[PDB]
Image (cartoon, coloured by chain):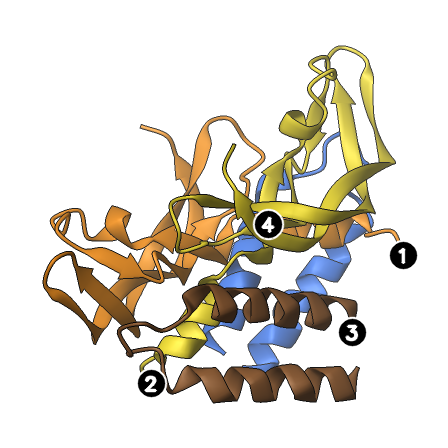
Chain colours: A orange, B yellow, C brown, D blue
Amino acid sequence: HEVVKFMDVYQRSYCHPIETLVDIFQEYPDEIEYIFKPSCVPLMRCGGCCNDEGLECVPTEESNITMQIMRIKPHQGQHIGEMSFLQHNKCECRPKK
Amino acid sequence: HEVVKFMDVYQRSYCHPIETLVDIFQEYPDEIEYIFKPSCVPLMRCGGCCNDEGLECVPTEESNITMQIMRIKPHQGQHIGEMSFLQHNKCECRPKK
Amino acid sequence: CAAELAALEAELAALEGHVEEADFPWGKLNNLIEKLWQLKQAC
Amino acid sequence: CAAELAALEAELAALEGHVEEADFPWGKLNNLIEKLWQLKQAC
């Protein structure tokens, strides 16, 4: 159990894409007829801190990823299909509006 | 851009400790006299999904980590000191109460 | 570590081809995935 | 990649010993940390 040095903490916590477990419903809000399995997916999304109240961490470049997801429709059946999700490639701390 | 196969998605999204950027204030709510830099830290914390409405992802074993953090007191000064945070070593999907 | 990891991975391999079967035991898979994550963290 | 990475890491090394100085330029450090993350993602 080594202690984490300040600059390493600071770099690791600063606004950047991090793997984030995101609910599929949230991304596909027009699909309330389905149950998704898994219900969430691991996506690279901006996170962390800016260390300035006047700034917020926002994406500046995006990309997409495809995953196999089971879609269940109650009282019909299920299938595994390919679903696309947005990822964040680059993040910046930029002024709050 | 290979598509992520179902079981890999399912394993990666299932309840387990994941690096999570956590606000220091949230962990140290008795310290409203200070500004912390960084304001957040990277901690292993349970996350992900259970794929069952009756269950929720909860820690079953915890540990601690120490990091160097700058503590700023307005109209006094600042110092870098060592601060301890809780981490989650093990997580399980267990019944909602 | 290596032995138990091998055992768990084989259990997962025997389940994973069956996930589309109507009556697949998701809870069994889920408990195994928890054991695999916990073993990787410990190892 | 290797060249630009080296340049950025040297810029970070020249700043990091100064973080406790009263007037340290946090915004400069922050912009560099954004460039380092973005370069690692691209590389």
Does the CB distance between marks 2 and 3 fall below 8 Å?
Answer: no
Q: Is residue A5 visible?
A: yes
Classify 10 Å Cα crowding around label 3: few (below 14), some (14-19), many (20 and above). few
- Residue at screen point 72% across, 31% down: D23
- Residue at screen point 60% across, 81% down: D3
Query: Mark 2 — residue?
Result: B2
Between circles 4 and 2, the one closer to the viewer is: 4
Q: Are marks 2 and 1 on the same chain?
A: no
Q: Quadrant of residue B28?
A: top right
Q: Is residue D29 left or right of residue D43?
A: right
Residue A88 placement (x, y as % from top left): 37, 59
Classify 10 Å Cα crowding around label 1: few (below 14), some (14-19), many (20 and above). few
The residues bearing labels 2 and 1 have C-alpha atoms spaced at a distance of 37 Å
Q: Chain of mark 4?
A: B
Query: Mark 3 — residue?
Result: C43
Residue B3 placement (x, y as % from top left): 31, 81
Nearest the camera: B32 or B80? Answer: B32
Three-letter residue code for mark 4? Cys
How many numbered marks are there?
4
Classify 10 Å Cα crowding around label 4: few (below 14), some (14-19), many (20 and above). many
Residue sticking out furthest to the front: C23
Instruction: Give the structural element (helix, strand or loop) at label 2.
Output: loop
A32 relative to A44, above or below: above
Q: Are marks 4 and 3 on the same chain?
A: no
Q: Chain of mark 3?
A: C
Instruction: Give the structural element (helix, strand or loop) at label 3.
Output: loop
Query: Mark 1 — residue?
Result: A2
